[PDB]
């Protein structure tokens, strides 16, 4: 027995390392693999400490859900998604320092690691998909695509969110408001780059 | 499996315009179609000794040459066989869906990309939640090839085509693959022998 996935208001945080490919070539398998595992370990810790749920890892990208499976208020979803994003950036510093003092970065034209983060709140079909084995709890829908594309539209080490997220964010933490057209998304989105600090 | 360097073949499948038919299937239709589709597709990969890495919406990632070793030529054969069987199964799925109201009221079609190359294969993530997957440019290439090919067609890189019988190559064209600075040699293969 299972539960039919259904529409639920959730918040999605999409993080993605900037140009991982280029360093996956500069560094070596063992280096790449270890840098990734440390990165993924720290980032997920951040998500977990903020009551978030790591939906999955898609390479060097992370998809975190807030409001599923555990219920969570709209404002709370956002507060935690942002706290998570801001906490990931602080952990990125320590990681780089460490990857620096090891040669994984800051040497051999391998710039220190940077990532993009997008946060969006909207409706999405959430639940178990696939088949009674390779079945997994995930979110399906346009809302998800918007988060991923906001991420690809923001500068390195910056956090971009949609208007639906910014409404719970203080004005003083808003760096820039923009009206962008995201790929695969017909209607333009009102976005805001938020301060990586509170 | 410990993250190690390895030559593998990556198969990337994706349904065309799944969203465009979302608010028509409703949450219930999306679920049933996706579940049925995923089941069959995963079967195709299974019957061909492939390893299902993960689903990403209506997209599927399969690996050949890991965890179990497999020769370069074998990888391509199994991968191409999987892709072809996928279309066949797609016929039947569409049939059933057809005489059901779900689709054809457009019918489901998908793209498939295939690339062979080095990649770090093994368990990544955390010492809580980790998953068997592949890392490296090769995955991007497979997915990008998947996005550039026409619906219900299989597109591969030159590294894969080098094992395919020439007569089965429907088209050779240099295309732009996002993330790849230089245009790549793409090969559309016959969906049949
Ligand atoms: N298991 C997996 N599933 C999907 N992609 C994977 C993967 N493992 C590794 N990848 C890889 O992760 C990399 C993503 O490419 P990047 O160099 O980081 C581009 P980017 O800087 O994020 O720019 P962009 O997102 O604006 O396009 C590719 O090398 C891709 O092949
Ligand atoms: N777990 C997940 N992670 C990321 N995206 C997900 C997802 N689950 C579902 N999706 C969604 O799955 C849908 C797939 O989009 P499609 O309309 O089929 C694009 P397409 O027709 O394949 O064109 P394209 O691949 O050439 O860009 C979107 O609604 C996307 O947001
Ligand atoms: C194609 C997609 C938008 C880009 C999303 C992405 C972007 C990115 O820059 C990454 O490094 C990784 C991902 C993984 C999921 C992708 C999504 C699947 C449905 C949607 O149409
Ligand atoms: C951004 C990406 C290429 C597109 C790949 C994709 C495409 C698509 O059309 C889908 O429906 C789903 C996916 C999931 C993984 C994506 C890959 C992650 C690394 C690489 O840079
Ligand atoms: Ca990346
Ligand atoms: Ca799709
Ligand atoms: Mg990316
Ligand atoms: Mg797609």
Image (tube, coloured by chain):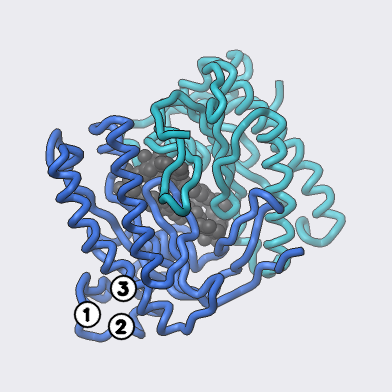
Chain colours: A blue, B cyan
Say whether mark 1 and mark 2 are on the same chain.
yes
Dot 3: few (<14), some (14–19), or many (≥20) neighbours within 10 Å? some
Q: Is residue B110 left or right of residue B144?
A: right
Vertical position of residue B18 compared to residue B115: above or below: below
Image quarter of the C terminus of chain B = top right
Q: Is residue A185 visible?
A: no
Do the residues under discs 2 and 1 have CB atoms within 8 angstroms?
yes
Name the residue located 85 percent from the left edge and 59 percent from the top edge.
B100
Label 3 – label 2 distance at C-alpha: 11 Å
Q: Which chain hosts label 2?
A: A
Dot 1: few (<14), some (14–19), or many (≥20) neighbours within 10 Å? some
Can you give x and y, in whole percent of width and height, for residue A193 in the image? Answer: 26, 71
Can you give x and y, in whole percent of width and height, for residue A131 in the image? Answer: 70, 52
Label 3 – label 1 distance at C-alpha: 13 Å
Can you give x and y, in whole percent of width and height, for residue A169 in the image? Answer: 30, 83
Does ligand 1 reach within 8 Å of label 1's beta carbon?
no
Name the residue located 70 percent from the left edge and 35 percent from the top edge.
B44
Closest to the observer: A181 or A196? Answer: A196
Q: Is residue A36 left or right of residue B65?
A: left
Q: Is residue B86 left or right of residue A57?
A: right
Can you give x and y, in whole percent of width and height, for residue B30 in the image? Answer: 68, 62
- Please tell me the numbered disc located at residue B150: none
Residue labelled with disc 2: A169
Q: Which chain hosts label 3?
A: A
Instruction: Please report whichever mark, 3 or 2, sits nearer to the chain's N-terminal start.
Output: 3
- Which element type, helix, strand or loop, lies under badge 3? helix
Front: mark 3 or 1: 3
- Please tell me the numbered disc located at residue A173: 1
- Which element type, helix, strand or loop, lies under badge 2? loop
Residue labelled with disc 3: A83
């Amino acid at each position: 027995s299972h539960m039919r996935p259904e529409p639920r208001l959730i918040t999605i945080l999409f993080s993605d390392i900037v140009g991982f490919t280029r360093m996956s070539n500069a560094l070596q398998s063992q280096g790449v693999a270890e840098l990734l595992n440390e990165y993924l370990g720290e980032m997920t810790r951040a998500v977990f400490e903020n009551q978030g749920t790591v939906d999955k890892f898609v390479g060097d990208a992370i998809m975190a859900l807030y409001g599923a499976p555990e219920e969570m208020s709209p404002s709370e979803q956002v507060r935690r998604a942002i706290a998570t994003a801001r906490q990931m950036l602080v952990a990125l510093e320590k990681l780089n320092q460490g990857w620096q003092e090891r040669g994984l970065v800051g040497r051999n034209e391998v710039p220190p690691v940077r990532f993009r983060c997008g946060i969006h709140q909207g409706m999405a079909v959430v639940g178990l998909f696939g088949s009674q084995e390779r079945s997994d709890f995930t979110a399906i829908g346009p809302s998800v695509n918007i988060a991923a594309r906001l991420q690809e539209a923001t500068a390195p080490n910056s956090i971009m969110v949609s208007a639906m997220v910014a409404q719970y964010v203080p004005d003083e933490e808003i760096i820039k408001r923009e009206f962008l057209e995201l790929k695969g998304i017909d209607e333009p989105v009102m976005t805001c780059v938020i301060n990586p600090n509170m």
